[PDB]
Amino acid sequence: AQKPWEKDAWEIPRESLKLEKKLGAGQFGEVWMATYNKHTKVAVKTMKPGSMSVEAFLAEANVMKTLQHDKLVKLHAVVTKEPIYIITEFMAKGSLLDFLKSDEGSKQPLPKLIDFSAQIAEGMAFIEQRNYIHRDLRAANILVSASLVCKIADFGLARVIEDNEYTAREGAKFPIKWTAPEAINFGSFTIKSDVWSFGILLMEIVTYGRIPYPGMSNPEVIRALERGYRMPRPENCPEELYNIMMRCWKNRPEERPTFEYIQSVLDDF
Ligand SMILES: CCN(CC)CCNc1cc(Nc2cc(O)ccc2C)nc(-n2cnc3ccccc32)n1
Image (cartoon, rainbow, N blue to C red):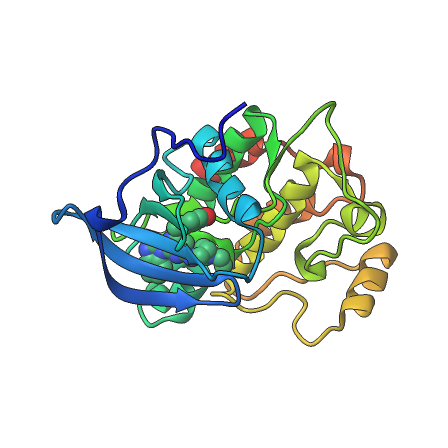
């Protein structure tokens, strides 16, 4: 059992970082662009003291220690005395959602969109293979590098899977338009419920960050899905890409495809 007062291999001294520019903020803290020991650009997430559990804030970095991959955002360090920091690689173009809604993201042609999709699929194939689930897959939680490599971020909800199902407690609420119906209705999270979110994420990419189910209410979405409705194919969406979405939105979790399969289809598009 680790002592509450002992540090680990990931710890760095606070003075090695110089926080240069605030990239964003929320109720739980801020994200800064920073340099580490002069020559190395990094990203820092700070926790707002009192906004949340310290142990939960830090638990995210523990997960990222385990889930290290080219297509997952890379943990470099932590600072575990208040103010509490998590340090990762810098991803110059920010979130995928904001990128696509920006001028540069808007100029990305279809082949690049499917490139982004394939990179994300690869990362999820790794999460699949490592017996984890993410549970918060969406464009907002993907980051994009200066050379246009997409990587999965936000591992706050990510969990190890024992025996192919995680069961959320009954009072858990999750972003409805992105969450698999069975996960919403009974708390049944599996890698197949991430497969569903990936379908929604595909739609986000091909629509340049447009919200899913535009103009529909959440209860309306839940009832539409039960009835068999699914989002229609956009103008710019190739049939083969929409058919993968549709496979990701099968009613029955076990009939949805594996991430390995999705990666390979998108790879060979
Ligand atoms: C993915 C978006 N969300 C939740 C919606 C997480 C917060 N935004 C972040 C996080 C991040 N790295 C990061 C990711 C984590 O999952 C945990 C800790 C950190 C530091 N880097 C960045 N980040 C890295 N380079 C950037 C350049 C511009 C804007 C943001 C940049 N942003």
